[PDB]
Amino acid sequence: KVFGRCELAAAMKRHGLDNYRGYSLGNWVCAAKFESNFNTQATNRNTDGSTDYGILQINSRWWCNDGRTPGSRNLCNIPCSALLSSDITASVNCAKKIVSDGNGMNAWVAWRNRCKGTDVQAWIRGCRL
Ligand SMILES: [Cl-]
Ligand code: NA
């Protein structure tokens, strides 16, 4: 599913991401925009053989099991395919664990390079939340 900007903002808010670990909603929407272009079905292979999945591009090296990333962890205890669902619940629950991991949202390269320090509130402007 390809979310609309405000549709995703509302879904994320409902799932408790607004201000989760101190990150306002705009940060999460911005991260999703640049990581997957709001597409829940996005996948991208990494050079180490792991693959990023879903709207937040969660990595199989540590957070989910895809059966093809030797010596990887499954810290979120879910098959990576669960992260591609039109229902973002799994992605959000796993993202909460990732952002609590110690490096905050810096875990998302696109957030660090394209959202961090920018006017992230603009990502939720105009939305009825
Ligand atoms: Cl932090
Ligand atoms: Na894994």
Image (spheres, rainbow, N blue to C red):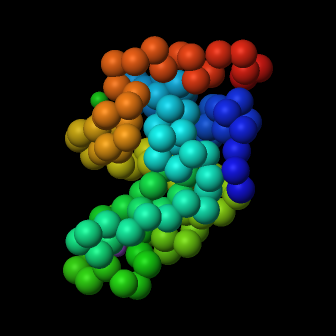
Q: Judge by depth and name the residue closer to the eye, 26 or 42.
A: 42
Q: In this view, does 55 lie to the left or right of 100?
A: right
* Picture coordinates of residue 117, whole percent (x, y): 34, 19
Q: Is residue 104 above or below residue 3?
A: above
Q: In which quarter of the image is ligand 1?
A: top left
Quadrant position of residue 22: top left
Q: Is residue 102 left or right of residue 52?
A: left
Quadrant position of residue 122: top right
Q: In this view, does 124 lie above or below 29?
A: above
Image quadrant for the N terminus? bottom right
- Can residue 36 be seen here? The reply is yes
Residue at x 46% of width, y 47% of height:
35
Residue at x 53% of width, y 25% of height:
26
* Picture coordinates of residue 54, whole percent (x, y): 53, 58
Image quadrant for the C terminus? top right
Q: Judge by depth and name the residue closer to the eye, 39 or 96.
A: 39
- Can residue 14 be seen here? The reply is no
Q: Is residue 104 left or right of residue 88?
A: left
Q: Is residue 60 left or right of residue 102?
A: right
Q: Is residue 108 above or below residue 116?
A: below
* Picture coordinates of residue 17, whole percent (x, y): 53, 34
Please give the count of numbered marks on the rendered protein: 0
Quadrant position of residue 63: bottom left
Q: Judge by depth and name the residue closer to the eye, 16 or 10.
A: 10
Residue at x 41% of width, y 75% of height:
65
* Picture coordinates of residue 110, whole percent (x, y): 37, 40
Residue at x 24% of width, y 39% of height:
103
